[PDB]
Amino acid sequence: AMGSMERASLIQKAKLAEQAERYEDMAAFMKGAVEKGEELSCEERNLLSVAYKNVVGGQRAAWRVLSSIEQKSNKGPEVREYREKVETELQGVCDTVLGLLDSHLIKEAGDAESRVFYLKMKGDYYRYLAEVATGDDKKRIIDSARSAYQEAMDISKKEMPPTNPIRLGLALNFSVFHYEIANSPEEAISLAKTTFDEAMADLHTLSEDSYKDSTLIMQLLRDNLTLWT
Amino acid sequence: AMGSMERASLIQKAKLAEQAERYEDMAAFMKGAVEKGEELSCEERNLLSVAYKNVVGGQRAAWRVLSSIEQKSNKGPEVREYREKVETELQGVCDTVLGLLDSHLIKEAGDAESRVFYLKMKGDYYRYLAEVATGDDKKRIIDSARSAYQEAMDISKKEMPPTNPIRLGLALNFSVFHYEIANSPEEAISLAKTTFDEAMADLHTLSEDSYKDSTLIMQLLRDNLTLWT
Ligand SMILES: COc1ccc(OC)c(NC(=O)COc2ccccc2P(=O)(O)O)c1
Ligand SMILES: COc1ccc(OC)c(NC(=O)COc2ccccc2P(=O)(O)O)c1
Ligand SMILES: [Cl-]
Ligand SMILES: [Cl-]
Ligand SMILES: [Cl-]
Ligand SMILES: [Cl-]
Ligand SMILES: [Mg+2]
Ligand SMILES: [Mg+2]
Ligand SMILES: [Mg+2]
Ligand SMILES: [Mg+2]
Ligand SMILES: [Mg+2]
Ligand SMILES: [Mg+2]
Image (tube, rainbow over all chains, first blue to last red; front, side, top):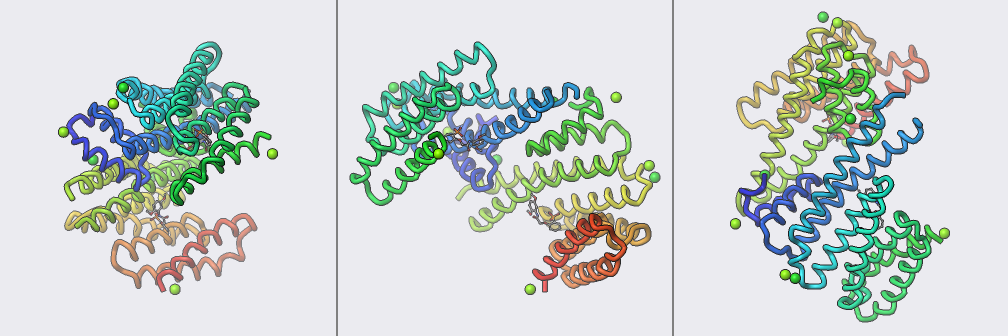
């Protein structure tokens, strides 16, 4: 439904929807913009990520509440039916994002900052699919997340400095994937520790604003390490 | 889309959606339940009010942000177009609620607690329509809100004690209608003061739990009076 709206107008409206905290609208404007077929700039990539993170984040929090209620009830079919409806809507949002990345954001992304950003996003949305998946397509979804994260880590370690915020946020989310999804808490702790230590040694190269950006994400790595150890 | 679901299952799902903070779902479940055609109980009336208050409250806050941005811009048509889209969606939610009340909740409501609750709701949703209305259908929408509120106040003063929470909340919202919509700050202050004073004189008749319920709303009346005087 956005094919008749100018790209620039979709971007402008996504920024208005963010101000208004209208995240489903923001995602629909940014999906529209991606579907224009042009590569996205840094600012536009961040608008796309912020919109979908907030939409799926609402769905994941609801699914958690419902899942907890369902597990306590284990009445009639209602809790299961409504948890299933929220789960399906979550899956649909993840499949939309994964489809934007496959058609055709990743294949057109040649620069490291864009290619790492989109492969981190692919890891993240398969990770949200894994949180609700049961059994053995669960395995295949977990390996798709791990593969995306690993491709992004390999490019990031060749092409970005250790304090780059996209590299830091990738490592943060890959560490969370290992602790919460892959049942690999030692890998999670090793990754978050190595990432933190390599960033700290590179901080001296930064300006004051870059230092603020990097140390913000380093504090997230530290906060997980405190929770995990 | 809820015609195939049991009434009891719609109520149960509205309570689950409230726990999950899924207010659009909660409203759609309660609309479904109303459309079964049976009168609603006290608890069910409160579920209907909580769902729509949260849905329209999100829309009103977004419309405020957008309207402020638009008034500052007075670029191209985008801010106006997106404010109009949020305004239209707000109007649609209000028209849905008003339609449930007209078809046929109010006409079947014979007891004072139900009839006052639904006429307060009718006042409230015409009040939200008035906040976004421009000119002379604006006048007619303001008079519809005032008429509904006045009918509810007349029943409430005949049939409920001055500390009844529905009577208090009606008077609170009618006072806000006079201050913010009707440009009648003196009427607003007179109503909120008379209501507060008549409730205070009736508190001695209450149990401890009823006293907690009434004094909570009295504090809201006091908070407005502090803001207005
Ligand atoms: C509204 O946004 C929501 C909603 C629900 C949520 O949990 C349900 C979360 N998650 C968090 O708050 C913390 O997650 C972290 C922490 C560090 C790195 C990556 C992540 P994530 O798992 O990609 O979000 C966010
Ligand atoms: C999310 O819920 C929202 C969203 C946006 C809001 O303003 C935009 C409000 N309003 C308020 O917080 C205070 O309003 C009062 C105060 C006293 C009596 C009646 C009302 P109301 O005007 O019926 O709500 C609530
Ligand atoms: Cl359902
Ligand atoms: Cl390429
Ligand atoms: Cl629009
Ligand atoms: Cl009747
Ligand atoms: Mg064009
Ligand atoms: Mg390219
Ligand atoms: Mg510890
Ligand atoms: Mg039946
Ligand atoms: Mg009746
Ligand atoms: Mg004062």
